[PDB]
Image: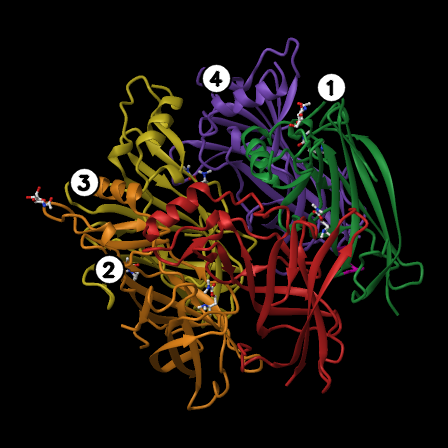
Chain colours: A purple, B yellow, C orange, D red, E green
Amino acid sequence: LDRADILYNIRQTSRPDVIPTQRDRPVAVSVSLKFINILEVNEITNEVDVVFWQQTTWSDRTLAWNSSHSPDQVSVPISSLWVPDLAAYNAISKPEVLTPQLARVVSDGEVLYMPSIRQRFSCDVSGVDTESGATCRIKIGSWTHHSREISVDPTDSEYFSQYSRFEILDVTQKKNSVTYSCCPEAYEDVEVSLNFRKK
Amino acid sequence: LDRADILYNIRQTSRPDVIPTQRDRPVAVSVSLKFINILEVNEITNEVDVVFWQQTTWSDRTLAWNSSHSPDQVSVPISSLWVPDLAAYNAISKPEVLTPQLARVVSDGEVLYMPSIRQRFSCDVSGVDTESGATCRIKIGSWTHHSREISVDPTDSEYFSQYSRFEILDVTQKKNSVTYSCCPEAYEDVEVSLNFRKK
Amino acid sequence: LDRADILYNIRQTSRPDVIPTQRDRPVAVSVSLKFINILEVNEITNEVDVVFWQQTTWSDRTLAWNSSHSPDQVSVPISSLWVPDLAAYNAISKPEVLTPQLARVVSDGEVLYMPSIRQRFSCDVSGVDTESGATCRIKIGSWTHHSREISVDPTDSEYFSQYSRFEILDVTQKKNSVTYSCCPEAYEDVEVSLNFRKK
Amino acid sequence: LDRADILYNIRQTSRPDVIPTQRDRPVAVSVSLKFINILEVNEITNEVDVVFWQQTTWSDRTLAWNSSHSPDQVSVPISSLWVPDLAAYNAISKPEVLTPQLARVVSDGEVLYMPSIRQRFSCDVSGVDTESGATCRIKIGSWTHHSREISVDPTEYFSQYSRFEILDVTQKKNSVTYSCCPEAYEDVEVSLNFRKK
Amino acid sequence: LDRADILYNIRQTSRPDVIPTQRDRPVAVSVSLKFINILEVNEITNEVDVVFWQQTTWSDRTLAWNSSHSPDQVSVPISSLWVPDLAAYNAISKPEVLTPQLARVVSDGEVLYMPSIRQRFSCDVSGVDTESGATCRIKIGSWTHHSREISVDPTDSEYFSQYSRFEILDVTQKKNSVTYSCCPEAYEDVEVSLNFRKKG
Ligand SMILES: *[C@@H]1O[C@H](CO)[C@@H](O)[C@H](O)[C@H]1NC(C)=O
Ligand SMILES: *[C@@H]1O[C@H](CO)[C@@H](O)[C@H](O)[C@H]1NC(C)=O
Ligand SMILES: C[C@H](CCOC(=O)N(C)C)N(C)C
Ligand SMILES: C[C@H](CCOC(=O)N(C)C)N(C)C
Ligand SMILES: C[C@H](CCOC(=O)N(C)C)N(C)C
Ligand SMILES: C[C@H](CCOC(=O)N(C)C)N(C)C
Ligand SMILES: C[C@H](CCOC(=O)N(C)C)N(C)C
């Protein structure tokens, strides 16, 4: 098998509309935000503009191939793959995807999709100009798949811009499972707490 | 039947361009706005920027399948389903859909579509800085389907952001059936009255 | 014939790229603006932001069907129909279509397309703050079809927002047939004069 | 032949990706800007926002049909035609096309494409508030086709409600060689002399 | 062969989703920014708005044809070609492509894609109003292809607008090969250092 064949097979059979559950277990999705920049804070309106890499991994066995005498990985357009329907609950703009929309697929079916995203959020900006800083919580999970279909789990300034007006003090993560009035089932989310301040 | 089969059949036969009327009864659509945020009020211009979940439900039997030994529900891209042509009469911007455009379909054909929307409206902003607050009325209904084809019915701070500069005092709903100069038939709408104030 | 059949036939045979002239007569298009809002006036720059329903009607016999024991009308995506190539000569932004892009088709081939549009225009804003008000003239006609192929004809505050900062005094319409330097034939337009003032 | 036939044939055989050179001569493209409005001048940043009709004509024989007992012209979506890859070198925003994207095609293969465009440019805005006015120069030519493949040549509607007025418009053709490439690329430079009223 | 045939073959067989590696060597991509304008500097936020031609070249032998009695080059929509997945790491807006999205392909499979791009960046704007000026560093590389699949290499005011409020003092380039926490492999990048200042 060469790359051409692998990409051909994936395109012909991938089923981007079909969540790749195994034996009625949820697809285990990992999410991890790598913050790159904080662009436009407003303590009055409690809105912040953030740029981050949304590192997202999950498994889709339907993509697997025998890697004997074959490449172990290919880059694939996400339009050819099932992708988790993650959304940020407290986003107040749609995600602006800054990078090429390609996912990396390993021969065993492991997928990594890691767009760089710019997005605005409604969160607690109070304290941003103090030494303790602000703590902005960003909430992410599947919009339409409950906990039996998708589980969501977590996996600081490492890639944060030195030229930002802000600095990151700490980043913490917490997993939740919430029942909403609209629906009987629970929906998982990750809450990423970004503790930052003006320099 | 597995998910793949169900989604395949739906894609192959769905008829997104065909309103699923039963026995010449209107498609009964329920609409309900869950307000998430109020972002940019202007009492001078009487314009407001709102984020809300537009909970929308209706029935389409053409989607139904036998759920015996099969999943009871699937998430489906709305491009593969008929969707009611709802519009907000007093919107002054097009709806920015913030979430993945997926509907949830149950085996009996019940559909739930619940995008998170950011949109600007022209409405009464007077009194927003008083204790009584402003009452902003949002009017939603089918743009091209009259009351024999589509009926529209309703179904507060529960999901409203604590970080908003505003707070919700009350939300009320009212159903209407209006005849317009352009056409002989009546068109139904729901009017959602959002009573809110600056904190 | 049911809706499914009618929409299937329309989709299979409609020819959205083909102007439905009959016997070498122009397609007679009617255009009528129902003003909904006036949002952002600037008497210095002579620019105005307007929301209006662009009521547009014409006939396309290729869409007709026998309505005996059949629905008399269907809603159809405009991407499946020929639509007149109307443009506003003095627009300075592209039309923001706020409503679902569906036209209503009657079994005899009458079409009604009535999007709600937000658009900015260059026009006479002088006097807007006086009692006489301003008169803003909006000019609309086929961009590429001359008078032998498309004719354009007209057909006040009825739907105008009570919450606008402005009010409508009067709306008048006038038909014209103009020869431009670019081309030998005449092109029809409708000029809609919107007389409005600050409240 | 009726319109439906002509449009069908064009759709089936047009080859929008294929530049219609004849006998290895360049496609001769005419370009002409009809200025409609000047919207947002900034003398400090030297940026201007303009609306103009970009009158563009060229010939594509592969579109031709026998007009005997047939319509002489049809309107065609540009997605079904080859169109010259013109760009404005000093544009600092992408062209906002305000009109329906249709070209007019004559039975002999003459094409006219005339979108109304709003676009921002980096140009000389100095003197806009004087009697001499500013002269803003707009430079347009094929982005990827050199002079042997595309030649570009120049060949009333300005809004009375603009804050500006047009004193003069002049045009000049150029053939320039760039560091990136061995061949010459043609352009038209349109000089818009305008001032605040 | 005429252009029609060449473009027809390319469209029918191009495989825009398939990186054209040769014998398991990386596709060697050259990148070079020709700066055209600097539009909106902010020394407080350290953000800059730049317009530049992103000269990008690489080889794709699957596009090659016999140029005997045939045109030596054609312009091709990039939607019909594989194109490197280059991204600017420090961009804070998506690239606004100002020009027609066509690449030039030579009969030997050499490709030149050279869009004009307007984009905002987070970079060091300090000193912009001084004689030394600011130095803004722009970092560009493949987003998803490591060094064994794509290598990235470099190739001043020449096309820079005389009407900008800024002027260019110097442009330097540096190639890097970086390993990120997310993945075991190294990813190459070019860092383009734009040294510029406000005029006056
Ligand atoms: C119209 O439909 C009806 C009922 O099926 C039929 O009686 C009539 O002949 C039809 N006319 C045409 C032209 O098909
Ligand atoms: C290249 O095309 C020429 C001209 O017809 C032909 O003579 C020659 O055999 C071809 N060469 C290759 C490598 O196929
Ligand atoms: C809160 C958010 C609401 C939107 O959900 C849907 O559209 N469903 C189909 C569940 N989910 C429950 C995470
Ligand atoms: C008021 C508003 C006007 C638009 O109507 C349509 O476009 N039709 C096709 C009816 N409707 C009737 C709800
Ligand atoms: C004013 C306007 C200019 C655009 O014309 C075209 O695009 N043609 C193809 C005629 N026409 C003459 C109505
Ligand atoms: C200056 C400008 C650069 C971009 O050129 C390309 O994309 N080529 C395909 C030539 N051209 C040469 C006019
Ligand atoms: C740092 C940056 C992050 C994005 O990576 C991807 O999306 N892969 C598919 C690896 N790359 C590795 C250059």
Q: Which residues are magenta?
A: E41-48
Disc number placed over residue A22 in the picture, else none: 4
Q: Are marks 1 and 4 in contact (CB under 8 Å)?
A: no
Q: Give amino acid for label 1.
A: Asp
The CA span between labels 3 and 1 is 60 Å
Instruction: Give above or below for C169 relative to A193.
Output: below
Disc number placed over residue B22 in the picture, else none: 3
Badge 3 and badge 1 in a common chain = no
Q: Does residue C69 appear to the left or right of A165 in the view shown? A: left
Chain of residue at mark 2: C
Residue B44 rendering spot, x and y as whole percentages: 50, 74
Residue E45 belongs to magenta span: yes
Q: Does residue A170 appear to the left or right of C47 in the view shown? A: right
Q: Are marks 2 and 3 in contact (CB under 8 Å)?
A: no
Residue C4 belongs to magenta span: no
Residue at x 30%, y 28% (from the top left corner): B107
Instruction: Give above or below for B118 relative to C178.
Output: above
Disc number placed over residue C23 in the picture, else none: 2
Between tags 2 and 3, which lies in front? 2
Residue D7 rendering spot, x and y as whole percentages: 39, 49
The CA span between labels 3 and 4 is 37 Å
Between tags 1 and 4, which lies in front? 1
Q: Which residue is mark 1?
A: E24
Q: Residue C38 is drawn in which quadrant?
A: bottom left
Q: Residue C157 is drawn in which quadrant?
A: bottom left
